[PDB]
Image (cartoon, rainbow, N blue to C red; front, side, top):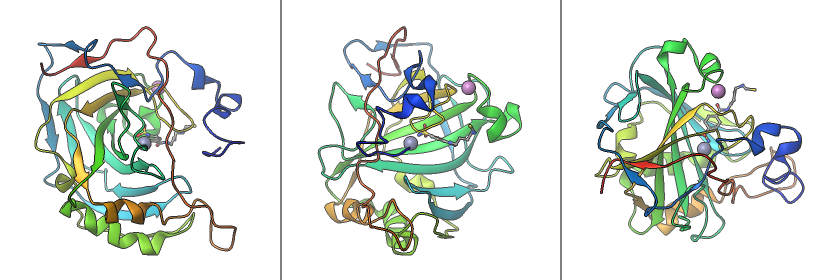
Length: 256
Ligand SMILES: NS(=O)(=O)c1ccc(C(=O)NCCCCNCS)cc1
Ligand SMILES: [Hg+2]
Ligand SMILES: [Zn+2]
C-alpha cells in the first residue's frame, strides 16, 4: 500500500476492508456543528520525563520513537479515562503548502499535521491496545507555514541521515514539549489509524491552535524518499489520507 494512483487510499479497502468502517479517520471538523461539551475535563500532557531513542524512515513517514517501558511522557484528562503512554510521533505533509494535513477544519487543509501517538496503559502494550476500542489516543496538531519552529530544527537537521526506506539514527534527548502550541483547546471524536491496518481504536484529540514552521523546514521533509537506497527515487510528499465520512458521530469541543 502507499499513496500512488495504483496503491493509494482508494485501493486500501481491498486488503483492509475496515477502510469503509463506521469510525474512520481523518475527517472534516465542521466548527459550527461541533458541540461545546462542558463536561470535558482539561487535557493533561505530561512530557517532562520523556526519552527519545531513535528516528526511522519506514517508507511512508519518519517516526521518532520513545522509551515507553515506564510512565515518562503521558497523556490524560480531557475525554480520556486513564493514562496513555507516548510511543512515537510522525507527520503527514504535502508537495505544496496548501495541502498535507489529514484532518481539515471547515474543509481547510494545512501544510502538514503532527501525530503524537499514545497507548492506554491498562492494556499492557501497544499490540494489546490495538485490540481495544479505547486503546489509543493520538494528539493531532496542525502545521502552517510562517516563522520557524525552533523546537523542530533538531528533527529537520537529522533527516539527511534517514533519506531512504529502512534507515534510522539515534535521536536521544529530544524534548517534545517544544512542538506544542500555547493553547490546549481541542476537538475530540472516536476514530482510527489513518494508515493500514486502519484499526478503530483511537480517541482523537485535535488541537484548535496550529503551530508555525518555516518554508525551509517543510522543504527538508520533501527531500526524503519513499523508496530504499538503490531504487528509483520517489520523493516522500503527499503522504496523507483524505477526510472520511463522519457517519453516526458527533465532534465535541472543549471551548466556545
Ligand atoms: N496515523 S495514526 O497516528 O493514527 C497511527 C498511529 C500508530 C500506527 C501504528 O502503530 N500502526 C502499526 C499497526 C500495528 C498493529 N498490528 C496490526 S495488524 C498507525 C497510524
Ligand atoms: Hg481496536
Ligand atoms: Zn499519522
